[PDB]
Amino acid sequence: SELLVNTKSGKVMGTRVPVLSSHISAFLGIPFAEPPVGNMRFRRPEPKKPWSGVWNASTYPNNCQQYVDEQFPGFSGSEMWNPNREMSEDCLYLNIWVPSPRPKSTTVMVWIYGGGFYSGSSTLDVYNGKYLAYTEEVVLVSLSYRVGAFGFLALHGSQEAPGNVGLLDQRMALQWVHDNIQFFGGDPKTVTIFGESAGGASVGMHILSPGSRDLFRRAILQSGSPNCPWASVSVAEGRRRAVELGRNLNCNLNSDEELIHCLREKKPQELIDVEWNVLPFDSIFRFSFVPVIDGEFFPTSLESMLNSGNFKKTQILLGVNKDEGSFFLLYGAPGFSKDSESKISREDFMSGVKLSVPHANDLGLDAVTLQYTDWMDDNNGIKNRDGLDDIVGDHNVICPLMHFVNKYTKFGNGTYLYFFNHRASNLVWPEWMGVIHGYEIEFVFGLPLVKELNYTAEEEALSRRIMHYWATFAKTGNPNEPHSQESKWPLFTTKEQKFIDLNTEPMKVHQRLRVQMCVFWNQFLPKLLNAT
Amino acid sequence: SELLVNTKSGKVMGTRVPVLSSHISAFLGIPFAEPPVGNMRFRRPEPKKPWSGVWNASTYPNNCQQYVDEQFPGFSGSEMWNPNREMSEDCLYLNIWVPSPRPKSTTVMVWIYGGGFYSGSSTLDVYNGKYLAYTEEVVLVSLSYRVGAFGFLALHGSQEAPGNVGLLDQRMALQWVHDNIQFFGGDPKTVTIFGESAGGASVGMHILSPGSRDLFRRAILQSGSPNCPWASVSVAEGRRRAVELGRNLNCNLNSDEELIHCLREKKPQELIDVEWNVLPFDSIFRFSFVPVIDGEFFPTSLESMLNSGNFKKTQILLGVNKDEGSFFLLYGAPGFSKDSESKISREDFMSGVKLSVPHANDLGLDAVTLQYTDWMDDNNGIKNRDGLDDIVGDHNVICPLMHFVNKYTKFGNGTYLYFFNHRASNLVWPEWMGVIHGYEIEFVFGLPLVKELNYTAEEEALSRRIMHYWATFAKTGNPNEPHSQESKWPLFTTKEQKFIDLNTEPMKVHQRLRVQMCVFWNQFLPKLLNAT
Ligand SMILES: *[C@@H]1O[C@H](CO)[C@@H](O)[C@H](O)[C@H]1NC(C)=O
Ligand SMILES: *[C@@H]1O[C@H](CO)[C@@H](O)[C@H](O)[C@H]1NC(C)=O
Ligand SMILES: *[C@@H]1O[C@H](CO)[C@@H](O)[C@H](O)[C@H]1NC(C)=O
Ligand SMILES: *[C@@H]1O[C@H](CO)[C@@H](O)[C@H](O)[C@H]1NC(C)=O
């Protein structure tokens, strides 16, 4: 049987799924770790014990316990990101889409979902890997990992809650892919990890971590970078937030053992209900429980690893969307709302700057405000709104990613950089938010190929071109077809720093993506804050 | 006789001078103070003792002792600024041009020359007041004042060299105009002081100083502002430079009396030869002996006088030239030269920034460099050259003048702002220097009306329009003719902040002259330096 696969952990039985009037095989909800429940909450994952019999891999698994966005009940724009299965701490499963007939040794792509390390599901309609596996003839894997406190509570020095266990969840799934994907027709020597947002940061963290480097061949990062300001905390700040979490739950704080024991007796929703109460500042684009710079997963600081070349040298493809910040301003910043144009007043602008750079002193806030204010037209509500959008996106996504790519290209083996700026014709979010955070995913996963979705013919053509870029990159290390007649995506080099736009228009090459602002965020402001 | 005028100091005999195929009267070299020679060097001026007989006022007086620019021997572009009479400490004289026939009670304009407070002459060909007096029918006065150490050596606390005596020279000339200009046909109640560069700063200093306010009606400032970074020093810094001056001349430094006595035994050229050796920094656009914030001429700091309204409230007309900085880069900055395009390398750019903001720490230098660097095109030699030009001009002239005008308009009675950006067709300086510092003076003094000078018909039309703006402003407080059909120069208001271009093209109104850069120079950088 095409749907029966024998693995080193046991046999699994998949299901035949239709896709664009054909069919492929899907193996949904394969366990890769022991359920991290009870006294294993906050612990490192353990490999799943082999099983006898046949694992029914015909339906999606549970999603991990997570905060659930209820800000717009019924609205698909936000609920498309919410968990669409029951939530459970028993949630360490992966899903595989496999071309039919079963390949022998084909390119493997492993998807790592984003969601700020506090949320995310592998089972979202927008992550359905069947279109990409079918169209490009690749083995498509999506893994899962613990998020929020369950994945990232960090009391460094203790072995019961060391931190980073959600990253270790991802690594263990990558280990299982390394060890078993051959039986599904995948080539364990040609595995590309790819992910968006926290998933893109995660991808970059596996490139850096010595314990993860050997488990994949190359990597794709979408709107995410390991050095992002929101993606990691120090050991001291991780400890402080874990203690504050227990303080919110009336825990005995006399020792790590007392605190962890208290936090394990709590129901999952009890932790989630107070999770946002431990942030140190009034802020947007900051999340409570994220990777910790521990000296283990990450042997030294991220910047010194980047500067010294202490990371996996391979090919990478990566990029950003035009309007990375609008998301977070809508949810947290005064003056923004979903059903208005969100024109911002000079005083809401200043409130927004403070929420966006919460670690800045007054001089730094002035530096930011000056950099993004048109003083011929300071009370222009559109300019203030788009200025804040740029501030949030530059500071949190684009300029960290540009710092990463410039450091990486010095030691790496090939870099391809993109700027995604097509706004989907069927977006339900307001126009002011622009090319939103995450709305390139549907093009990467081939959703425009499904008529019922609406989607213009030009958007289907864009999706196919993007899918073939990603999959050709995964297969060869280069998104371009050799000897093809199509425009060519040029290499990003230290000298030229070229990149392409991704949209429905003929390809255009540019250089030095947002270099003016990123010199401010990467060189000047950090220097200003350290001196003052 | 039309050429004989009896004054309160004695009778004076002028000369009939031809002008544009007509004639007017000129009274050149009228003494207004006692010669500040010998033991009166560095002292306050004393009024000139009345004389018997007739003072021969037919020829120009001596120029004050000053540094003489020899950087380009023979070149008219630089020598047109050098003294064109013998130099002498006996140099406190004024010149009057008087329409023919002698008026009864007409508008008076008093010209105060610039030259960084270290140089300047009232007798320069470009200051010949006969064209303006003839064309606009006004009494044109040009005064003189001590410059360099002779005018501004400041040992505060001592009465022998208190500082500011060059400003007191100007005031005493204004007193003499107040007291005697009626006998030449001038209206002592309608006197406009005007000046360029240090002369424009001087004008603003008389607006501020309680001891000068009553001696004039309104004021014109060209490319100069009392708050300019180069126009004043503290009492401590003035004392330090005076002591360093004596150290350069092997003076006894045990007391003020010993130091002043030593400096008075020195020949004028001995002081001039070492004058540039006392500057505290490697710098451009900084001069050794300038006005001192003494608590007398200026009762408090300039900024607190400006903020509290402690100044003469009247009408002012003022403005700047497009390329205020190119002058000083040519003479002092590496990579600039007179006979090349002066394309600047990224490292000469950084050297120039340091010379231009000598009081900046490293963080401030970074802030400036960032503000003026196009990081898409950092090695563009033209952009680096023009960037430095803007840095020098914004920091030293334009943004101080914009701070002054914005503070003044809050309490004043009418403000007219201009931006002069016509490059004269006959300029002998290289094209890269643009609309140079001081090359609007020839238009203010009507030189384009003289055919022999070359000068296009459009430049003659510009000169006449400018002369009539200045003279109508002097007469009424408003540069525009009432009920005329011509475009109207609008008032500068706190709310709108309108100004006009001055060039050969049809008038255009703009708002917020160089506001982006001036917010950097007037608000952010000062804040950055105070915190760090
Ligand atoms: C696998 O589980 C689903 C869950 O209800 C069930 O409907 C399906 O029939 C099962 N298949 C097998 C072969 O047990
Ligand atoms: C990648 O590495 C190989 C050698 O292993 C080298 O030949 C090739 O030029 C490299 N490519 C880039 C883009 O650095
Ligand atoms: C005034 O002085 C000049 C200087 O040489 C002289 O040529 C002229 O004749 C004098 N005029 C009178 C009236 O003394
Ligand atoms: C100037 O002052 C007079 C009163 O003395 C006033 O009527 C006039 O409006 C003022 N003009 C401006 C421009 O402030």
Image (tube, coloured by chain):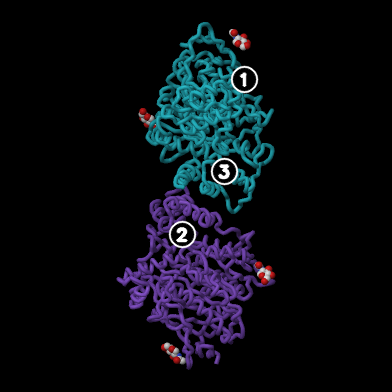
Chain colours: A purple, B cyan
The residue pinned by badge 1 equals B85
Q: CA distance from mark 1 to mark 2?
A: 64 Å
Q: Secondary structure at mark 2?
A: helix
Residue A515 figure quarter: bottom right
Looking at the rendered image, the disc whose residue lies closer to the viewer, 3 or 1, is 3
Q: Work out whether B464 lies above or below B59.
A: below
The mark tally for this picture is 3
Within 10 Å of disc 2 (Cα), the crowding (few <14, some 14-19, many 20+) is: many
Residue B270, position as x, y percentages in the image: 60, 25
Residue B255, position as x, y percentages in the image: 48, 26
Q: Where ligand 2 lies, by image quadrant?
A: bottom right
The kind of residue on which mark 3 rests is: Lys
Residue under disc 3 on the same chain as residue under disc 1 = yes
Host chain of mark 1: B
The residue pinned by badge 3 equals B354
Label 2 CB sits under 8 Å from any ligand 2 atom? no
Host chain of mark 2: A
Q: Secondary structure at mark 3?
A: helix
Looking at the rendered image, the disc whose residue lies closer to the viewer, 1 or 2, is 1
Residue under disc 1 on the same chain as residue under disc 2 = no
Compare residues A380 and A396 and report the one nearer the observer. Answer: A396
Residue A61, position as x, y percentages in the image: 44, 82
Q: CA distance from mark 3 to mark 1?
A: 37 Å
Compare residues A82 and B394 and report the one nearer the observer. Answer: B394
Compare residues A190 and A329 and report the one nearer the observer. Answer: A190
Q: Which mark is drawn over residue A180?
A: none
Compare residues A332 and B41 and report the one nearer the observer. Answer: B41
Left or right of A333? Residue B468 is right
Left or right of A73? Residue A26 is right
Q: Residue furthest left?
A: A250
The residue pinned by badge 2 equals A392
Residue B155 makes an appearance in the image: yes
